Length: 123
Image (cartoon, rainbow, N blue to C red; front, side, top):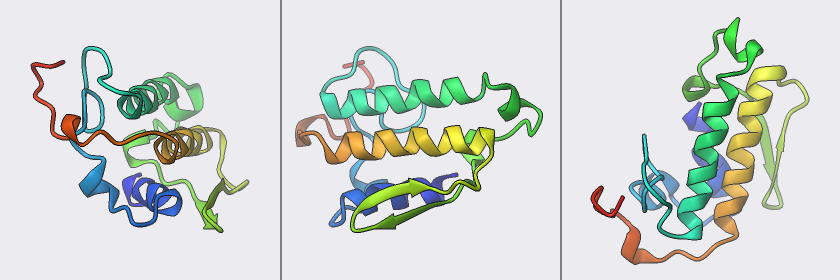
């Protein structure tokens, strides 16, 4: 679930408004995403991606047949650091960790404005 993923990124990157800034970026931030990541910040996404391809291979994610893209785990934010609650069970726990490494990834790398809204031909 996305209500919570965008909350992660505003936890870490506060002046952020992530649906707005980190959408449509380089080859991977946004749905689908092909070719080679244009920058680190895009690789970030490139990775988060493989992490949701991952999850769904999971057997738990299976027989809850769960929706990553609908994953409703639970995390907490404080003093700008993230914790996905122990209460998350095998699947949405995985999913929680995907959004978590990506969200930090992002706080961690430079934001080249010129690959914001890249053209799917550069990919």
